[PDB]
Image (cartoon, rainbow over all chains, first blue to last red; front, side, top):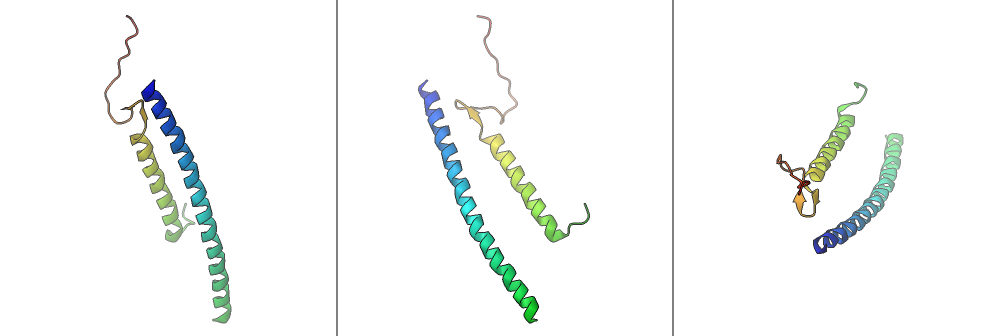
Length: 50
Length: 50
């Protein structure tokens, strides 16, 4: 039972940590998407100015 | 399909590669109370007869 509860607590905490990783990836991809929007505006401006 | 170019094909390719890496990871890191189940071809015997 001691080994069992050790595994249980470890797996629960690891699942929580995976959720935190999901959140980090989400915020990073949001920043990347806004950078992509800026790049698209730059590309349109270049097509205009060419 | 043939409508997608190589630049459009690299995305599908790296997604497939990430999925395969995840498959390998979950195949190699799943264990029940300290013994793995997807790493060896050995059989398990359960004493069910006294």
